[PDB]
Amino acid sequence: HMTDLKASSLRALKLMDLTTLNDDDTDEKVIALCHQAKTPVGNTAAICIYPRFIPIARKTLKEQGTPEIRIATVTNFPHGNDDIDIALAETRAAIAYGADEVDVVFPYRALMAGNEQVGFDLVKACKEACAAANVLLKVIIETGELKDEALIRKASEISIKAGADFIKTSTGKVAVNATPESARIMMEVIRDMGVEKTVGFLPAGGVRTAEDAQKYLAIADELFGADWADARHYRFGASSLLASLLKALGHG
Image 1 (tube, rainbow, N blue to C red):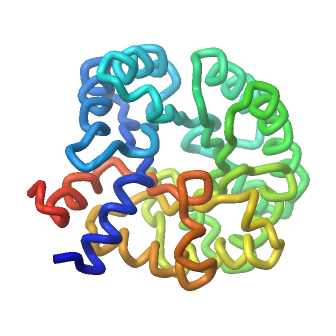
Image 2 (image 1 turned 60 degrees about the vertical axis):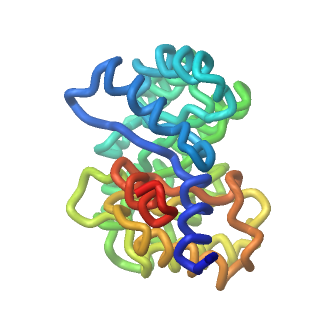
Protein backbone atom coordinates (compact mmCIF):
# COMPACT_ATOMS: atom_id res chain seq x y z
CA HIS A 1 0.00 0.00 0.00
CA MET A 2 1.93 3.07 -1.15
CA THR A 3 1.54 6.13 1.11
CA ASP A 4 2.91 9.66 0.88
CA LEU A 5 5.14 8.99 3.89
CA LYS A 6 6.59 5.76 2.37
CA ALA A 7 7.22 7.53 -0.95
CA SER A 8 8.95 10.45 0.76
CA SER A 9 10.92 8.15 3.00
CA LEU A 10 12.40 6.10 0.14
CA ARG A 11 13.33 9.34 -1.66
CA ALA A 12 14.94 10.71 1.44
CA LEU A 13 16.94 7.51 1.97
CA LYS A 14 18.33 7.65 -1.55
CA LEU A 15 19.20 11.31 -1.08
CA MET A 16 20.92 10.90 2.27
CA ASP A 17 24.44 12.04 3.17
CA LEU A 18 24.71 9.51 6.03
CA THR A 19 26.92 11.24 8.59
CA THR A 20 29.22 10.64 11.53
CA LEU A 21 31.12 13.74 12.76
CA ASN A 22 32.04 13.04 16.39
CA ASP A 23 35.18 13.72 18.44
CA ASP A 24 35.33 10.05 19.36
CA ASP A 25 34.97 8.67 15.89
CA THR A 26 37.18 5.77 14.91
CA ASP A 27 37.80 3.57 11.91
CA GLU A 28 35.47 0.93 13.36
CA LYS A 29 32.58 3.43 13.62
CA VAL A 30 33.19 4.65 10.07
CA ILE A 31 33.26 1.05 8.75
CA ALA A 32 29.94 0.43 10.52
CA LEU A 33 28.54 3.63 8.92
CA CYS A 34 29.55 2.38 5.50
CA HIS A 35 27.71 -0.88 6.10
CA GLN A 36 24.63 1.09 7.30
CA ALA A 37 24.62 3.04 4.00
CA LYS A 38 23.96 -0.17 2.09
CA THR A 39 20.31 -0.78 3.06
CA PRO A 40 17.82 -3.48 1.96
CA VAL A 41 15.94 -0.96 -0.22
CA GLY A 42 18.90 0.89 -1.72
CA ASN A 43 22.03 2.83 -0.94
CA THR A 44 22.29 6.32 0.49
CA ALA A 45 23.68 8.93 -1.87
CA ALA A 46 26.76 9.54 0.22
CA ILE A 47 28.45 9.33 3.55
CA CYS A 48 29.84 12.37 5.38
CA ILE A 49 32.86 11.80 7.63
CA TYR A 50 35.94 13.66 8.85
CA PRO A 51 38.70 13.74 6.22
CA ARG A 52 41.09 11.36 7.94
CA PHE A 53 38.55 8.55 7.60
CA ILE A 54 38.16 8.88 3.81
CA PRO A 55 40.69 6.21 2.78
CA ILE A 56 39.27 3.52 5.07
CA ALA A 57 35.70 4.45 4.07
CA ARG A 58 36.63 4.17 0.36
CA LYS A 59 38.09 0.73 0.93
CA THR A 60 35.05 -0.40 2.90
CA LEU A 61 32.56 0.87 0.34
CA LYS A 62 34.50 -0.86 -2.43
CA GLU A 63 34.66 -4.19 -0.62
CA GLN A 64 30.94 -4.30 0.04
CA GLY A 65 30.22 -3.60 -3.62
CA THR A 66 28.92 -0.02 -3.33
CA PRO A 67 31.64 2.13 -4.89
CA GLU A 68 28.97 4.56 -6.14
CA ILE A 69 28.20 5.82 -2.62
CA ARG A 70 29.92 9.18 -2.59
CA ILE A 71 32.27 10.31 0.15
CA ALA A 72 31.67 13.80 1.51
CA THR A 73 33.63 15.52 4.19
CA VAL A 74 33.78 18.84 6.02
CA THR A 75 36.26 21.69 6.10
CA ASN A 76 36.54 24.99 7.96
CA PHE A 77 34.37 23.04 10.39
CA PRO A 78 32.38 23.64 12.49
CA HIS A 79 33.44 27.15 13.37
CA GLY A 80 33.38 28.92 10.00
CA ASN A 81 36.46 31.01 10.69
CA ASP A 82 37.51 33.64 8.18
CA ASP A 83 41.10 32.45 7.53
CA ILE A 84 41.07 31.55 3.87
CA ASP A 85 44.51 29.96 3.88
CA ILE A 86 43.43 27.46 6.55
CA ALA A 87 40.13 26.62 4.90
CA LEU A 88 41.90 26.13 1.59
CA ALA A 89 44.61 23.93 3.07
CA GLU A 90 41.94 21.76 4.70
CA THR A 91 40.06 21.56 1.40
CA ARG A 92 43.22 20.60 -0.48
CA ALA A 93 43.86 17.89 2.10
CA ALA A 94 40.29 16.58 1.79
CA ILE A 95 40.80 16.33 -1.96
CA ALA A 96 44.13 14.53 -1.46
CA TYR A 97 42.58 12.05 0.94
CA GLY A 98 40.12 11.20 -1.86
CA ALA A 99 36.92 13.13 -1.09
CA ASP A 100 34.22 13.22 -3.73
CA GLU A 101 32.56 16.24 -2.08
CA VAL A 102 33.64 18.90 0.41
CA ASP A 103 31.18 20.73 2.71
CA VAL A 104 32.90 23.96 3.74
CA VAL A 105 31.60 26.27 6.45
CA PHE A 106 30.98 29.82 5.25
CA PRO A 107 32.55 32.60 7.41
CA TYR A 108 29.17 33.58 8.78
CA ARG A 109 30.42 35.60 11.75
CA ALA A 110 32.39 37.77 9.37
CA LEU A 111 29.27 38.40 7.30
CA MET A 112 27.33 39.24 10.50
CA ALA A 113 30.07 41.80 11.19
CA GLY A 114 29.55 43.33 7.75
CA ASN A 115 32.27 41.59 5.70
CA GLU A 116 30.72 40.11 2.56
CA GLN A 117 33.98 39.88 0.66
CA VAL A 118 35.77 37.29 2.80
CA GLY A 119 32.98 34.73 2.35
CA PHE A 120 33.09 35.25 -1.41
CA ASP A 121 36.86 34.88 -1.47
CA LEU A 122 36.83 31.82 0.82
CA VAL A 123 34.17 29.93 -1.13
CA LYS A 124 35.79 30.89 -4.48
CA ALA A 125 39.23 29.61 -3.38
CA CYS A 126 37.77 26.33 -2.20
CA LYS A 127 35.64 25.99 -5.35
CA GLU A 128 38.65 26.43 -7.56
CA ALA A 129 40.53 23.60 -5.83
CA CYS A 130 37.49 21.36 -5.88
CA ALA A 131 36.61 22.02 -9.50
CA ALA A 132 40.15 21.24 -10.62
CA ALA A 133 39.80 17.85 -8.89
CA ASN A 134 36.24 17.08 -10.07
CA VAL A 135 35.02 17.44 -6.46
CA LEU A 136 31.68 19.06 -5.62
CA LEU A 137 31.60 21.92 -3.13
CA LYS A 138 28.80 22.36 -0.66
CA VAL A 139 28.70 25.52 1.47
CA ILE A 140 27.31 25.44 5.01
CA ILE A 141 25.95 28.89 5.87
CA GLU A 142 24.83 28.17 9.47
CA THR A 143 21.30 29.50 9.32
CA GLY A 144 20.77 29.05 13.05
CA GLU A 145 23.54 31.48 13.82
CA LEU A 146 22.78 33.96 11.03
CA LYS A 147 19.14 33.96 12.15
CA ASP A 148 17.85 36.88 10.14
CA GLU A 149 16.26 36.23 6.75
CA ALA A 150 18.31 38.93 5.05
CA LEU A 151 21.57 37.41 6.27
CA ILE A 152 20.49 33.88 5.25
CA ARG A 153 19.69 35.21 1.81
CA LYS A 154 22.96 37.14 1.56
CA ALA A 155 25.13 34.22 2.66
CA SER A 156 23.32 32.01 0.16
CA GLU A 157 23.74 34.54 -2.64
CA ILE A 158 27.44 35.12 -1.97
CA SER A 159 28.07 31.40 -1.85
CA ILE A 160 26.28 30.84 -5.16
CA LYS A 161 28.11 33.69 -6.84
CA ALA A 162 31.42 32.26 -5.59
CA GLY A 163 30.60 28.88 -7.15
CA ALA A 164 28.86 26.71 -4.53
CA ASP A 165 27.45 23.51 -6.04
CA PHE A 166 25.13 23.12 -3.02
CA ILE A 167 24.03 25.35 -0.18
CA LYS A 168 23.60 23.57 3.16
CA THR A 169 21.76 24.94 6.16
CA SER A 170 23.89 23.96 9.10
CA THR A 171 26.76 22.18 10.71
CA GLY A 172 24.62 20.24 13.15
CA LYS A 173 26.92 21.56 15.89
CA VAL A 174 25.05 24.68 17.03
CA ALA A 175 21.76 24.99 18.90
CA VAL A 176 19.52 25.69 15.90
CA ASN A 177 20.02 23.83 12.62
CA ALA A 178 17.63 23.06 9.75
CA THR A 179 14.15 24.51 9.92
CA PRO A 180 11.45 24.52 7.24
CA GLU A 181 11.54 28.32 7.11
CA SER A 182 15.32 28.38 6.60
CA ALA A 183 14.99 25.76 3.90
CA ARG A 184 12.34 27.82 2.14
CA ILE A 185 14.45 30.95 2.30
CA MET A 186 17.51 29.23 0.85
CA MET A 187 15.55 27.51 -1.91
CA GLU A 188 13.96 30.88 -2.76
CA VAL A 189 17.49 32.21 -3.32
CA ILE A 190 18.16 29.39 -5.77
CA ARG A 191 14.87 30.31 -7.48
CA ASP A 192 15.58 34.05 -7.47
CA MET A 193 19.03 33.61 -9.01
CA GLY A 194 17.68 31.14 -11.56
CA VAL A 195 20.32 28.56 -10.60
CA GLU A 196 18.05 25.53 -10.22
CA LYS A 197 20.24 23.60 -12.70
CA THR A 198 23.57 24.19 -11.00
CA VAL A 199 22.91 24.57 -7.25
CA GLY A 200 21.45 22.03 -4.90
CA PHE A 201 20.03 22.33 -1.40
CA LEU A 202 20.77 20.39 1.79
CA PRO A 203 18.81 20.61 5.03
CA ALA A 204 21.13 19.41 7.75
CA GLY A 205 21.23 19.12 11.50
CA GLY A 206 18.49 17.76 13.67
CA VAL A 207 16.59 15.97 10.88
CA ARG A 208 15.70 12.82 12.81
CA THR A 209 12.36 11.43 11.76
CA ALA A 210 10.68 10.35 8.55
CA GLU A 211 8.06 13.06 9.17
CA ASP A 212 10.82 15.69 9.42
CA ALA A 213 12.26 14.61 6.11
CA GLN A 214 8.84 14.72 4.54
CA LYS A 215 8.47 18.42 5.45
CA TYR A 216 11.61 19.37 3.55
CA LEU A 217 10.81 17.41 0.41
CA ALA A 218 7.37 19.01 0.44
CA ILE A 219 8.95 22.48 0.16
CA ALA A 220 11.32 21.40 -2.61
CA ASP A 221 8.51 19.85 -4.61
CA GLU A 222 6.35 22.96 -4.20
CA LEU A 223 9.06 25.30 -5.38
CA PHE A 224 10.73 23.33 -8.14
CA GLY A 225 8.36 20.48 -8.97
CA ALA A 226 8.69 16.94 -7.87
CA ASP A 227 11.46 15.92 -10.30
CA TRP A 228 14.03 18.51 -9.23
CA ALA A 229 15.27 16.82 -6.08
CA ASP A 230 17.74 14.25 -7.40
CA ALA A 231 21.12 13.55 -5.88
CA ARG A 232 22.83 16.45 -7.72
CA HIS A 233 20.22 18.87 -6.38
CA TYR A 234 19.18 17.61 -2.95
CA ARG A 235 20.58 15.70 0.00
CA PHE A 236 19.61 15.09 3.60
CA GLY A 237 22.56 15.73 5.89
CA ALA A 238 21.87 13.41 8.78
CA SER A 239 23.52 11.22 11.40
CA SER A 240 20.32 9.93 13.01
CA LEU A 241 17.58 9.76 10.37
CA LEU A 242 18.09 6.46 8.56
CA ALA A 243 16.60 4.15 11.13
CA SER A 244 13.38 6.19 11.13
CA LEU A 245 13.18 6.08 7.31
CA LEU A 246 13.69 2.30 7.28
CA LYS A 247 11.02 1.88 9.95
CA ALA A 248 8.58 3.94 7.86
CA LEU A 249 9.34 1.60 4.92
CA GLY A 250 8.77 -1.55 6.99
CA HIS A 251 12.43 -2.44 7.75
CA GLY A 252 11.31 -1.52 11.24
